[PDB]
Image (cartoon, rainbow, N blue to C red):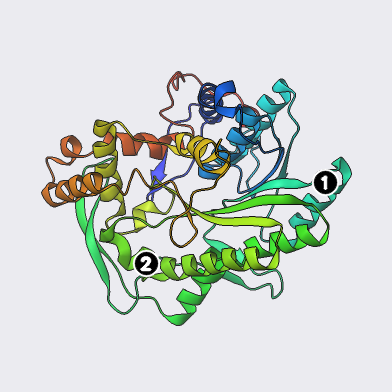
Amino acid sequence: MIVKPMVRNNICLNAHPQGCKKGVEDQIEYTKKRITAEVKAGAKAPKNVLVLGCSNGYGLASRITAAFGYGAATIGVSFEKAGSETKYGTPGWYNNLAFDEAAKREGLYSVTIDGDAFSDEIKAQVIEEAKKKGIKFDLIVYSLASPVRTDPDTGIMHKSVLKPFGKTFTGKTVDPFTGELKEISAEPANDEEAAATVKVMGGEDWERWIKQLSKEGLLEEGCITLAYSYIGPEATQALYRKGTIGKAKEHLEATAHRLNKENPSIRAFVSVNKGLVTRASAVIPVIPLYLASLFKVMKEKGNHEGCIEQITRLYAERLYRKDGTIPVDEENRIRIDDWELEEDVQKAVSALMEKVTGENAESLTDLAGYRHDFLASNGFDVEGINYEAEVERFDRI
């Protein structure tokens, strides 16, 4: 069985087990070189970390940075599909396996809980695991990437949508594989859609995790909790500020404020991260063209970051600094999109988006970098992996 990427409806349908593994190992290796003795010396360190959404992207990087950077014990939660002998698991399933294996090889405590993180069943499972080991958490990272949430008190399922308000949102977009430029649109959402999105992307579950953990006395004094979010460029403020996403963000930010007021011994932040290729990226106008242009501009400037570069910087230069402060903006958010939103960067990116055409997209923007990030998420196009070799089982890594 030769496994090559199968992409349809802008989604990569399969995954490569050894590729996903090499991907995790590469992040671990970077972490070991980035988070050195000097970087840690004189700063505090996380000891027991809970990561909700630990199998991909920022969540996975957060777990790797905690464990292999700072030597912390970690419990990760994610909802994956296991693989069988002949059927693909989700990429996150192979990522978790690779993580737990490396953690064990290093003698680090690591436990992965697979299930719906929005459910009280899973929360109860973390709680009992913590009480057994005698763990109290000092860092809780909320990085849940789901388009749907089944409300645990009412059982009804909500799905988020990505739409503006009042006026339809139209803009250029690009296919990184073909090079095709198009114009697509997002029509204004209704109340049902807006309310569903808030339900999925807001801070309801974040708060629920904190309260249940609090009641069971599983939060260490001074415990940091973070939720990842995105603000983005001016070109997409219609969705990220005044769209359905913007409303969910406002809810998440209000949730963070309330967590700080109700738990005096806690430090809760929304962490605003940089833009990267996500599963949803292809359905949003402007975004795929923005990212390709951002990648080009930042790689040329020399400050391009992927997930693990972002999060290691988050730990070393926001959470665990030697001056003991946690720098925030005027609204008390941690900002690591500071490089992305630099004036010179955004100006050049905008110029690039204005100039892009059909024949020049490949050379003007970084579609190649975009393709790589898209594929690497599922374990494809990873350096050092043969890909012409057959995979015996989809049961191991």
Q: Residue at x 58, y 63 (%)?
A: 256
- Secondary structure found at label 2: loop
Tell me, for residue 268, which label it has, or none. Answer: none
- Secondary structure found at label 1: helix
Compared with residue 191, is residue 303 higher up or lower down, i.e. above or below?
above
Mark 2 → mark 1, Cα distance in angstroms: 39 Å
Compared across the picture, whether 232 is left or right of 213 comes to left
Front residue of 179/153: it is 153
User: Residue 288: image x %, image y %?
Assistant: 30, 49
- Label 1 packing within 10 angstroms: few (<14), some (14-19), many (20+): some
| The C terminus, quarter of image | top right
- Check disc 2 and give the amino acid type: Arg
Front residue of 376/245: it is 245
Return the disc, 2 or 1, that comes first in the chain's sequence.
Answer: 1
Q: Which residue is mark 2?
A: 241
Does the rendering let one see residue 336?
yes
- Check disc 1 and give the amino acid type: Glu
Q: Residue at x 73, y 25 (%)?
A: 104
Compared across the picture, whether 209 is left or right of 288 comes to right
Q: Which residue is mark 1?
A: 129
- Mark 2 or 1: in front is 2
Front residue of 221/275: it is 221
Compared across the picture, whether 172 is left or right of 337 comes to left
Question: In this view, which residue lies farthest toward the right?
Answer: 132
Q: CB atoms at circles 2 and 1 under 8 Å apart?
A: no
User: Residue 378: image x %, image y %?
Assistant: 48, 37
Does the rendering let one see residue 98?
no
User: Residue 325: image x %, image y %?
Assistant: 55, 45
User: Residue 84: image x %, image y %?
Assistant: 66, 37
